[PDB]
Amino acid sequence: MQQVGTVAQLWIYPVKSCKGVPVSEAECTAMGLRSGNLRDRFWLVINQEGNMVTARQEPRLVLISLTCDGDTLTLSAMNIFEMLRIDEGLRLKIYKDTEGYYTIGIGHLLTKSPSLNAAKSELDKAIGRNCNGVITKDEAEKLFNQDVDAAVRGILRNAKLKPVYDSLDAVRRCALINMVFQMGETGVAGFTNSLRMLQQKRWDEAAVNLAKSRWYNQTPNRAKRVITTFRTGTWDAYTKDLLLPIKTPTTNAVHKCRVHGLEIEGRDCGEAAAQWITSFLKSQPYRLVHFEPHMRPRRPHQIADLFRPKDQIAYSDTSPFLILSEASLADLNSRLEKKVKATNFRPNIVISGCDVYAEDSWDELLIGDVELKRVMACSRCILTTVDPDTGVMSRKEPLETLKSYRQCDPSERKLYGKSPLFGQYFVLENPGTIKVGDPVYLLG
Ligand SMILES: Nc1nc2c(c(=O)[nH]1)N[C@H]1C(S)=C(S)[C@@H](COP(=O)(O)O)O[C@H]1N2
Ligand code: MOO
Ligand code: MOO
Ligand code: MOO
Ligand code: MOO
Image 1 (spheres, rainbow, N blue to C red):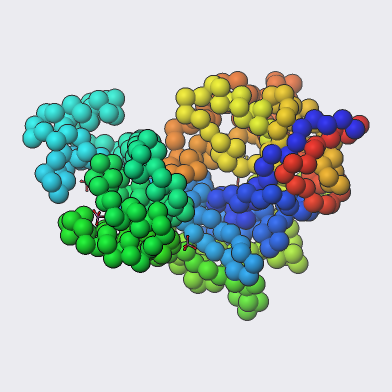
Image 2 (image 1 turned 180 degrees about the vertical axis):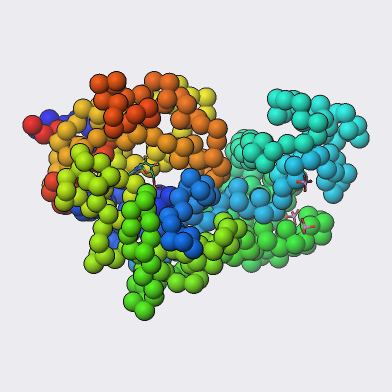
């Protein structure tokens, strides 16, 4: 009867622990959200023993997206960070770059001075400790995220690069950032003709012209990859996207998998998917499986007895739904140095227009014709610390901050123990469709 908020985002995470898919409408099913063929945690990566592989084991799973376009599923994993990792490589000790300048990490220039002392002083200043010329991969990734951020900041303040950048699609934007990271903003701003052809979408002409530059001559193999990316607008020069059919042949094997200790089947999605995931993670042999509706689902009441005996899920942790408010997220953000997005907490329904943590008090919600019933709070873990853009798991922000102020009340410590509360689990009371913009009504 009374409105307590509005749906602001809906997210489906088709493969467990991988990138969310934002949607404007979704059907609410007893097992979670569905948008056509994409259903929430209906796909799972497993190892050779059949055990789940989650972002706890492989934080780079958050980089992988499974999306659907009509007919075909696409698996894709590339973004600017991964593109530059491939092009810049990784060195944990000070080395000289190809122009003789001291550098470290992922292409991080320390100084143009010939003094190794100046390079070490710059390294200790940048990392904040006495490194003795050596860093950890985590520290290289920290410098790298700062360096990419600085390159995009630079493009957006540059009058010659900004209009090109803004005209480019998301993949070709990454090729322009890649150039700026390598050669700096002034250098890239100098390619007057190639920049013109890019802004005009004359991709073959721009590819031909950029291959005549001095850049190409100095690093032709890297230039050829950035060029292909501008020519095609695809990731064919890097981890190329894999296109699979929506329907998996029923001749493919059904595996007995284990998710959070409980058994569940999944139909193997085929060798191309397995090789693609394994290659990208550089891991032991993994497979991708998909839950089909005739398989026995997992039972949340076996995981937490507050759930009803009839509740069912495929591969999610515990619940068919997680709901979070924008208010709760803006709150945590007013306490954090590095800001986080709803994506860190993996909610399916994000609700705006309410007071902080209002969702903890919402026992029964009507959204459209969908009714949802609150079961319990979502208690948080290290998965919240995996950065969704870089795939790097941090040292516990934002978990530590959550820990400081969002613990469960002693009167309640048997479900949650100590693990901070951020988001609420819900189940379905009536099926239907929900849309971004739907008012949310608190019932009873
Ligand atoms: N639908 C749903 N969303 C959820 C949960 C859940 O059990 N069900 N658990 C949450 C927790 S605590 C975590 S760590 C992440 C795990 O996401 P994954 O299952 O895709 O790895 O989903 C979050 N959102
Ligand atoms: O092989 Mo290195 O230069 O320690 O990363
Ligand atoms: O003007 Mo260039 O430097 O032919 O792109
Ligand atoms: O951005 Mo384009 O001209 O459709 O390939
Ligand atoms: O960075 Mo390369 O392999 O010289 O083109």
